[PDB]
Image (cartoon, rainbow over all chains, first blue to last red; front, top):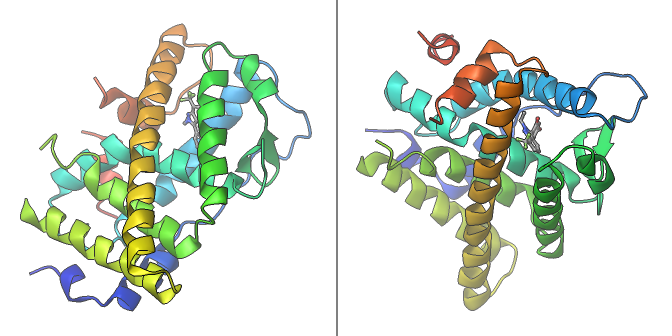
Length: 235
Length: 10
Ligand SMILES: CCn1nc2c(C(F)(F)F)cccc2c1-c1ccc(O)cc1O
């Protein structure tokens, strides 16, 4: 029996909160990137170091440790980019029109233009960020969404355990909304709005994955073995 | 033998 299902809503929240990975910095070089090499280099470098934290974060997500190593591997390989992206969007909320990859790295669509097929993804990321902002997404909600992506994205490509743990997180989201004074109707409407954004997050992940693949074939920007293997799992 | 296999252990 998994411990996750025995946790209370409040016991689910401060665990996800406490499990949060830190906000990493990019190179301290003050040169605004415009080339693909410089931009993607900074992005992949940051992604590399974030992946290490994401891995130790996932292990802190209730119910995740109760999975087989193989399942844990499959879920991370499937959701890693979705997880990186939703984190990017969350950090970018307070910076309209900007993408805060790192406190010392904010990019706009003008810099995405200098990389074919990148601007479209930026616009999608910016739109998602904007959406998060207008909904006044709360940190407690964000952490719940991120965990849902981890357990959901690869749940099929494989049982009740994950479904039960996902239900548990659903209870926690409603809990947060009720605790925030939302009406019963406002609760299920916001729940729906939040979950529907995951569809768009998945979309951006799949588009980003394709772009990262072609980039791998051009073999200009160096990719870490970890990124390659994570990226590899998507074929 | 994935790097991910190793990192998930430690
Ligand atoms: C390297 C991961 N990555 N890839 C991104 C792309 C892609 F795939 F099209 F190249 C577009 C936008 C962001 C991308 C990221 C990424 C996302 C979040 C983050 O914190 C770091 C990143 O490199």
